[PDB]
Length: 34
Length: 34
Image 1 (cartoon, each protein chain N blue to C red):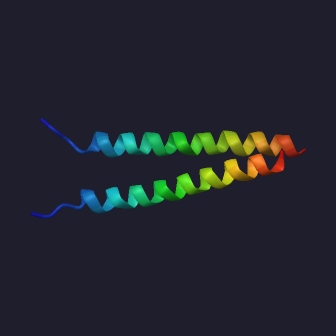
Image 2 (cartoon, rainbow over the protein chains, first blue to last red):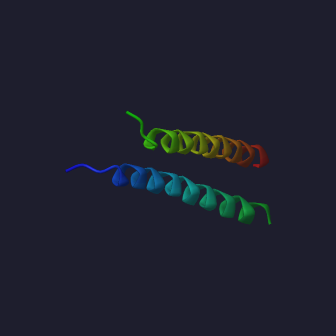
């Protein structure tokens, strides 16, 4: 019993984690300027 | 024997490479300001 939904799902989680890291960095620098 | 998992997979790799390039640019400019 094998499926490829979970691996592309985990790719979605890791790219979403990268997006969340970029959002944290952008909000951090956006408060660092002003 | 053909599958469409690899092409969407390679799309995920190239968009993740673009995300990694954006992360490098954001960390670079974030160190360039301060």
